[PDB]
Image (cartoon, coloured by chain):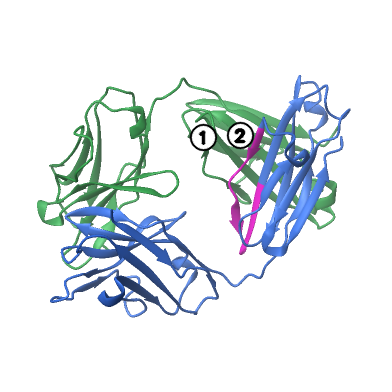
Chain colours: A blue, B green
Amino acid sequence: EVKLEESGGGLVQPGGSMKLSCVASGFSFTNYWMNWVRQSPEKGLEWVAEISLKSSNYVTYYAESVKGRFTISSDKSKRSVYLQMNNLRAEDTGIYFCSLWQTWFAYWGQGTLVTVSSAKTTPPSVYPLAPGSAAQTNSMVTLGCLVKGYFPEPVTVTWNSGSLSSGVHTFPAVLQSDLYTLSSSVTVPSSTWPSETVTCNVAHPASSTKVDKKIVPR
Amino acid sequence: QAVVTQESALTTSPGETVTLTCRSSTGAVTTSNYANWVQEKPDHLFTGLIGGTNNRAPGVPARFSGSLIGDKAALTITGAQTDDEAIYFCALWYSNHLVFGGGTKLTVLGQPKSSPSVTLFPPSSEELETNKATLVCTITDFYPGVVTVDWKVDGTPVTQGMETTQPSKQSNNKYMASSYLTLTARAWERHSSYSCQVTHEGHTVEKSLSRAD
């Protein structure tokens, strides 16, 4: 079967460069155009560039936003297409995909993440979230745990070291000022808290940081 | 630059017919834009459905079809199924470049309506020591997965400092999302009443908290 394998993504300062590689394996793709499409949380899909995989006939199209900056190229002997990125900006962050196109987009790669950011590796500040007196009367009590100012993704949140698995809700990370922030909550019976302790264990492998935060009544 | 627009969201039920559209700002979409349609499911899953306006790639269920409806290209799912819930991207060719649209999030009713469970958390004493204050409004177990979040401080709506996440599918395929109201420590001392109003399917749930206690 066909299989596209992508590689060469990572973190890079603005103005820097990166070159990705999409390795195609299968039957003869002389009849396909290899596309690069990037996906960001802010612009969904965004077509970047494309090349015709005819060894006889090479044609390239680029998106207006990458003209003069990006260049697409292929090497048959390696069965590979490449995207050269220069003068990268923050708007170029996203999961870059390669796709074989003939009439329709017939095959896709797994994608590789390209992050354009100047921020440094920053560990999270774990703050406890506990109900107010307006929320001390419910049969079930929702405790929480704010994870603020960390970089890069991901962090992993577990409650009571995994022994508290049902009722957990980890929310999507938001980004502000080159720094991430997400929250995780756990809802337990009001008979278990504060009688029994409840603790969020956050891990940030990038900074080799683990923080345990016990939720005590306010 | 050859902007392509699609309905941001549409909702259908199993067995019904739904029609997404695709409008070009240059003018009428024509067969010569060779309109494409790409289905995206969670986990960056991608499938090419339609090419050249109405060419269905192999393996794509017969209930999918591409066509023009006036000045737009149109994807038509006839007799939808629960596994059709996904994002559907339209792409038009413009002579020397392709352009994707914003996409359309199609919901196929797979379970009954569930109202959101809202919970409001005040700033931690730890965080205030950084002269920063963040209120956290959690939202879980709502279906379909679209919510609106409005903040009031001392009865006055807030325009700035708020940020809400895009919903996320739970194991039960209900949805969860979190909103944040970011304040200065001072600003948190300067006011007494804070509200998080979550509207879902035209019904609003509110959670407030007062520092006067």
Helix, strand or loop for disc 1 = loop
- Chain letter belonging to callout 1: B
- Callout 1: 10 Å neighbours few (<14), some, many (20+)? many
User: Quadrant of the rendered structure where residue A168 is?
Assistant: top right
Does residue B145 show up magenta in the picture?
no
> Which corner quadrant holds the C terminus of chain B?
top right
The residue carrying mark 1 is B147
On the image, the x and y values in percent for residue A155 come to 66, 53
Q: Amino acid at mark 2?
A: Ile
Magenta part of the chain: A168-182
- Specify the farthest residue to the left: B31
Circle on res. B112: none
Q: Nearer the viewer, residue A131 or A79?
A: A79
Tell me which secondary structure the magenta stretch mostly adopts. strand
Left or right side of A11 for B194: right
The residue carrying mark 2 is B139
Q: Nearer the viewer, residue B195 or B163?
A: B163
In the rendered structure, which disc, 1 or 2, sits on the residue that comes first in sequence? 2
Question: Which residue is located at x 17 percent, y 67 percent?
Answer: A30
**From the viewer's perspective, is residue B134 above or below residue B14?**
below
Helix, strand or loop for disc 2 = strand
On the image, the x and y values in percent for residue B17 come to 24, 27
Q: Is residue A96 in view from this perspective?
A: yes
Distance between mark 1 and mark 2 Cα atoms: 9 Å
On the image, the x and y values in percent for residue B85 come to 37, 34
Left or right side of B151 for A56: left
- Specify the farthest residue to the right: A195
- Check contact, mark 1 vs mark 2: CB within 8 A: yes
Mark 1 vs mark 2: in front: 2
